[PDB]
Image (cartoon, coloured by chain):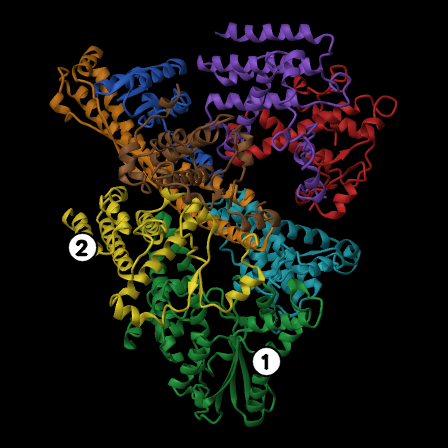
Chain colours: A blue, B orange, C green, D brown, E red, F yellow, G purple, H cyan
Amino acid sequence: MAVIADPETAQGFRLAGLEGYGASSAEEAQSLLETLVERGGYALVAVDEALLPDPERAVERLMRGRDLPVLLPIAGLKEAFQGHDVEGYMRELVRKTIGFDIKL
Amino acid sequence: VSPTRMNLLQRRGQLRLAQKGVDLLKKKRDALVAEFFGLVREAMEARKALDQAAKEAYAALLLAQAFDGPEVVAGAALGVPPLEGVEAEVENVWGSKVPRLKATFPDGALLSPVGTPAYTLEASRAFRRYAEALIRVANTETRLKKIGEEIKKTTRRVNALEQVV
Amino acid sequence: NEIAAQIARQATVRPDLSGEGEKEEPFAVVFAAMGITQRELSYFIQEFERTGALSRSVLFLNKADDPTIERILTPRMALTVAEYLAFEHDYHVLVILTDMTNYCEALREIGAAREEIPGRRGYPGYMYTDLATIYERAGVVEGKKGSVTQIPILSMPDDDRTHPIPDLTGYITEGQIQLSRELHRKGIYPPIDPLPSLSRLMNNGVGKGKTREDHKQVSDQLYSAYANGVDIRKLVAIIGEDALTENDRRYLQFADAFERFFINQGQQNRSIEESLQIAWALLSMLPQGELKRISKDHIGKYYGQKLEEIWGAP
Amino acid sequence: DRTHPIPDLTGYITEGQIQLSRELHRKGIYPPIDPLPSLSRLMNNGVGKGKTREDHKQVSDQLYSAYANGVDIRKLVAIIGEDALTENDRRYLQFADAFERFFINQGQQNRSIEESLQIAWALLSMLPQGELKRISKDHIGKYYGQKLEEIWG
Amino acid sequence: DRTHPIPDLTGYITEGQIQLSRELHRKGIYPPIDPLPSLSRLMNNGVGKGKTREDHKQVSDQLYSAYANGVDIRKLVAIIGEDALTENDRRYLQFADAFERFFINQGQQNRSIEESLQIAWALLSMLPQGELKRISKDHIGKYYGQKLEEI
Amino acid sequence: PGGDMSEPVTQSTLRIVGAFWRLDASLAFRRHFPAINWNGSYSLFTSALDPWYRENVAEDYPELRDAISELLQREAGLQEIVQLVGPDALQDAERLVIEVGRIIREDFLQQNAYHEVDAYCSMKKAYGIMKMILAFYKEAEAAIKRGVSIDEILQLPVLERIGRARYVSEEEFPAYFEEAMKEIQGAFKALA
Amino acid sequence: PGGDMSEPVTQSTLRIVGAFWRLDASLAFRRHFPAINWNGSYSLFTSALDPWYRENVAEDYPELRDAISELLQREAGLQEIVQLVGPDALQDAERLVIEVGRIIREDFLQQNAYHEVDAYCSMKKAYGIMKMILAFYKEAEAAIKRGVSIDEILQLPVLERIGRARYVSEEEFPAYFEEAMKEIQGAFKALA
Amino acid sequence: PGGDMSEPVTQSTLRIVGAFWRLDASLAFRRHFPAINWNGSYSLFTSALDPWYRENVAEDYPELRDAISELLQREAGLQEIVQLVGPDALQDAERLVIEVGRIIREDFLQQNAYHEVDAYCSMKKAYGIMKMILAFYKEAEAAIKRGVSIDEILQLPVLERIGRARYVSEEEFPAYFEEAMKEIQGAFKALA
C-alpha cells in the first residue's frame, strides 16, 4: 500500500502502483504514519530505516487497537546502494528476544 | 487453611503438581527456542533477498530518471492506477494468530502507462519484484515476533511459578 | 491379593541357567495372612487348591475377627517354619506376608492395652525393632544350601510414603515394588509402576553366569526409554503431535506399546527368556543408534525382532 | 475455621447452617451470607405446589449451579489473562458479579418470596435458555426473559 | 526462619537486630549485613550534633531510601526486562551495585565513622543533587563533593 | 470430625469393608448430588460380578464400564494441565476428552433423589445411557480426525437428548434409546 | 508468638473488643509506619460516630472517608494484576488509580511519631488532606478523559504540595489548604 | 530417610563437623567418580592449613586452588545458557570457560579407584596438574584474544598429554610435568 522513503523511491513506488510518500525527517514521517493509520492504510506500511530506526515508536499509541498493519524498516534508494548490515539488526533482535548474544 | 493431616497431603500434592507444571513449561520453552532459531535463519535469508531486489530495482530506476525525462517517468507513474488491496490471511502460531500478508496484482504490464520508454518500464517490474520480496520479509518478521512474544511469556510464567508459588 | 497369589503359584528357581542342570534343591512357599476377611480367605483357599500349588505350601491364616495376639504371633510362626525348613532340609523358601499394616495396627493396639506411652504418630516406640526382628530373619548362610526370601506386602494408609509403616519398612528392606492406581484404572494388570520401583540387590543376582549377559543393560535402557516417553506424552497434549520430532513420536509409541504389552501380561506365566524377548521386540521400535546404554555386541545379536509374542499366549 | 470442634459438632447435630463470609463483608455486601457453604436440610419439605411457588426448587438449583460456575471461572481469570475468556465464561463472570451485587446485597429491606423469585429470574435471564439444564421448559417459558433494570428504575 | 521461637523471643526483648543475608554472602560481600531488615531503636538518641557529625541521621535516611529504591528497581527488572528503564531507574540500579560493592563490602578494614560518612557521601553524590530529598540543603554542598571513592 | 479421613475409625473401617463410597464436600457445595468422590472410591466386588452382568444385563457391559472408567481416568489426568495453562491451550482431542468427561459427570453420574423418575434407575437404563455416550464419543473423535472444529460438535443438538435421557421413564426408554442411537448415527455419518 | 494470629490469646481477645488494629511485619520492615494493615483491621464504632463527625468536623466527612476506602480497595484489587502482567499493559484509568492509591498510602496514612509537627494531627487536617486528594483525583480523571497523558500528570508540581501537607503546622494549615485547592483546580484548568 | 537435609540429626551434625563431602547419585549416574558434588560441599580447615601447604607443597598452592575454584564457579554460573541455547551458540570466551571446566572435571576431579596408579595421588601431582591446566587456560585465552578460533584450540595435541597426566606414576611425574609445561607454551607461541 504505502511506503515512506525518499522522493525518488516514492516516485518508483508510484511507478509500481504503491502509494509512495516523501520525507526527510522524523516529524513528517510520523505525521504521515499517523494519517495513514487514521485513514485506515491497509496492512503493510514500510518506512525507510535511515529515516526512522523503529516505526513502532509511532505505533505505541495505536498498536493496542489493531493488528492488521505490519510495519518494518527498509533501506532507501541511496542507502541500498551501499552495504547494509542486516546481520547486526538480527543480532539486536535476538538479544532483545532472549537477552544474550547468540553468535560469534 | 485449617491445619489437618488431609490438608497437609493436599498441599504436598499441589507442590508436586506445580513442580511437574514447571518442568512441562521448560520443555515447551525449549521447543519454542528450537523453532525460533529456524525462524531467525529464514528471516536472514529473506532480508538478503529483499536487499538484492532493492539494489536491482534502484539500479533500474536510476537510468529512467536520467535517460528519460523526469516528467516522463512521473507521468508513467501517475498513469498506472495505484496498487490497492493486501490480503491478510490468518496463520496459527502456537495458539496465537498472525496475519499472513499477500498482495493482489493487476497483472502489471497490462496496466502499462503512456510512459513507453524501456528504461522507465524496467524500473516498474523491478519495483514489483521488490514489493514481492518485501511481503515475504514482513511475513517472516511477524512470525518471528510472535514466537519471541510466546518465549517471553513462557519464561515469565516459569519464573513466576518457581519463585512465588 | 491377586499379585500375591500369582507370585505364590508361579515362583520357581532356574538351576539350568546357572549351569548346574539339576533341580536338587527343593522349593517351598510359606504364606502368612494377617487380618484378612472371609472373602480373602476363600479366594486364597480356592487359588491354592485349584492349581495344585498347595502341595508345596504352608498357610498361616489369621482372620480379622480373630484375637490380635494371634495376629502378632502369625508371622513369627511362619518365619520359624521357613527357617526350620531352609536351614535343616536345604530348601529354598519364599515367605509372603499379606498385610503388614494390619500387623502394625495390632501391635499398636496391644501396646495401648498394656498402658505404654506411644511414640511418633501414636505408634509404639519399639516398632522399628519389632519390624527388624521380623524382616532380618531372611538371608543366606555360609555353608548352608538353603535360603529364605521375604516379600512383605503392605497397604500405605493414605498413599503416603512418609507414613511410619512404609517409612520404616523401606528403611529396613532392600527396595520396593510400587503399584500404580493410574495403571489399575487404565485396565492394566498387574499394575506395577517401573519408575518408582527399585531392587537394591539386582546387580548381584544377574550377569553372565546367571540369567543372561544382557539383562542389566536391557533393564536400564527400558527404564530410560520409558521415562522419556512418559515425559513426552505430557507435552504432546499441549503442543500437538505434529510439532514433535520423529524421535519424540518413536518414544511416545514405545511408551504406549510398553504399557500395553510389557506391564499388561494378565495371568500369563512368563519365563525370563520370554520377558527378555518381549523387551527386545519393544526396544526394536526405537532407532538403531538410540540404544546408547547397550553394547554393540548385544545389539548385533538381538536387535530387529518384531512384536509377535503377546499374541502367542491369549 | 469450619473444622473447629464447636462448628463441626454443631453442624453434625443441627439441620443446616447459615455461614457468613468475610470476603463479602469487606466489599460492603449485607447480609454477607455465602450461599455455597450454607445449607438447609428441611428446605424441600416447605416448598412445592401448595407451598410458595412451584418453580422454587429448580430455580434454587440453577442459581447454585450458575454461581458455582462463575466462582470457578474467577479462579481461571486469576491465573490467565481476562481477555482470553470465551463469551460464555464472560457471561458467567458477569452473572456472578450481578448476583453478589443484587441478590445478596439487600440492606435492611424486607422482601417477599415473589419479589426474590422475580430477582432470581431476572438474574437467570442473563444466560441463554440452553444453559438452564436444571429447570423444566414450562417454567422457562413462563418466567424467562424479564429484565433486571425493569424491577427498579 | 525468623519466626522460630529463639529469634522471635529474642526480638521481643532487645532494641533491634542486625540481620545477615545469604545473597550477599553468595556475592562474596563481607560482612554480609542486609540493611533493609535491620533496625536500631535507640539510634535516634545516640547520634547527632555533639554526639557525631550533624548530618548522620539525614544521610542514614537517604541511604536507606536510595537502597530500597534500587532493590525495587532490581525486582522490577527481573520480570519485565531492562529496556523499559528510565535514566533514573538505571541510575538507582547502578547505585545499588556500587553500594553493595563499596559501602558493605569493607573486608577486614577498621573504618572510622568519618571515613564511613565520607564514603556514604561519595556514593550519594552519584545521584542528582535534587534527588537527595531527605537531606537538607545546608549539608548538601558542604558534603556533596561530587567525587568518586578514593579507595 | 472435620471431614478428616485420617481419623482412626475411618482408617479401621477402610481395612475391613469391600466397598468404599467417599463423599466430597466440594460437590455438595455445588449441589452436584449424590456427590460421591470418584477418585477416592473403590470396590473389590467388580470382578466377581461379571458373569451375572453378562447373563442379566448385556454381553459387553463390563467392556463399556471399563471404557467409561478409562475415560474418567484420562480426564482426571488432563485436569492437571487444564488447571495449569487453561482449557484453551489444549489440542482438540484433549478438549473433546474434557467435554466428554463433563458430559459423563452431568448426565450419567448425577442423579436427583427427589425427582419422580430419576430417583430410581435400572441396570439397562444406565447401560443404554453409557452406550449412547460412548457412541457419541467415538463419532466425535472420528469427526475430529476429519477436521471438524470442536465448537461445532459441542453445538450438535443430540447433546440435549443425551442430557435429558436421564429423565425418561423406564417404559418409554427402550424406544427412546433406539431413536437416540439413530439420531447420533445421523448427526455425524449422514452429515459427513 | 511468631506473629501467628490463631494464637489463643489473640482469638480470645478478638471476641470481646470493639476495634482491631492489626500490625503487619511487612510494612514495618520497609519502615512504613504506623504500619496498620488496613485490609485486616476493622472497627465497630464507625457507624455510631457519624453524627458527631457531621456536627464537629464536616457535613460530608463520612462520604469522603468512604471514597478514600473505596480508592484503597480498588488499588488493592489492581496491585495483583500489576504484579502479574506489569504496569506497561494497563490503561490510563487504572494507572491513575494506582498512583492515587500510592499517594494516599505515602502522604495520608504515613505518620512520623518523632517529627515535631507530624507526630500529631487534628481531624480537620485529615479532612483537608482527604479533600485535596479527592479533588486531584477528580481533576486527573477528567484530564485523562480529555486525552492527557498520565506520565504528564505524574510530573505536575502540585503533587509535591499534596505530599508536603502533613508537615505543615496546625496554625498554618487552613490557609495552606485553600492555596492548595486553588492550585489543584488551576493546574488542570490551565492544562485544558 | 528421604534425603532431606533438614532432618534434626543432619542439622545437629553439620553444626559441629569441620567439613561436609556431599556424595551425589546424579554424578554417579553419568559415570563420574568419586562422585562428590563440589557445589554443595565445603570445608572450614583451609585457612588454618594454608601455611603447611606453603611450606610443604608450594608457595603459590593456595592461589592455584582459589583459581581452580573460581573457574569451577564461573563454569557453573553458565549452566543456564548452555542448557537453554546450546554450547555452539556461545561466544569464544564462554565456550573456552565451558571447555576448561570440562577438562578440569574429566582430568583432575575424576579419579579411578580400581586403577593401579590412579588410585592414589599425592599433593605434588595435584599441584602439577592444576598448574598445567591453568597455564593452558591462560595461553588459550591469549590466543582467543589474538583472533584464534576455539575450534582450532580444541584440536591441539597437548590436550591428550594433559588428559593422560593422572595415569603417570609417582616417581616419573616430575619429568612428564616439565615436558608438558614446555609443550603447553610451545603449542601456542610457536604457532602464533
Viewed as shown, does residue C1 lie left or right of A67? right
Give yes or no for contact between labels 1 and 2 (Cβ–Cβ under 8 Å).
Answer: no
Depth order, front residue of E41/A91: E41
Q: Quadrant of residue E22 in the image?
A: top right
Measuring 40% from the left and 43% from the top, which residue is drawn there?
F86
Q: Which of G53 and C96 is in front in this view?
A: G53
Q: Can residue H109 be seen in this view?
A: yes
Q: Residues within 10 Å of mark 2 (few under 14, many from 20)?
A: few
Residue C292, quarter of the rendered image: bottom left
Disc 2 target residue: F175
Q: Residue at x 13, y 20 (%)?
A: B112
Does residue F154 sit above or below A82 in this rendering? below
Find residue D54 and report its horizontal and vertical position in percent: 34, 38
Instruction: Give the residue at the far left of this rendering.
Output: B110
Residue type beneath disc 2? Ala
Which residue has dot 1 on it? C70
Does residue C80 sit above or below C203 in this rendering?
Answer: below
How many labels, in total? Answer: 2
If the image is split into quadrants, where does the N terminus of chain A sit? top left
Kindly state the secondary structure of the residue where label 2 is placed: helix
What is the chain identity of the residue bearing mark 2?
F
For image coordinates 71% across by 15% down, the residue present is G122
**Residue C89, x across and y down, in percent:** 55, 94
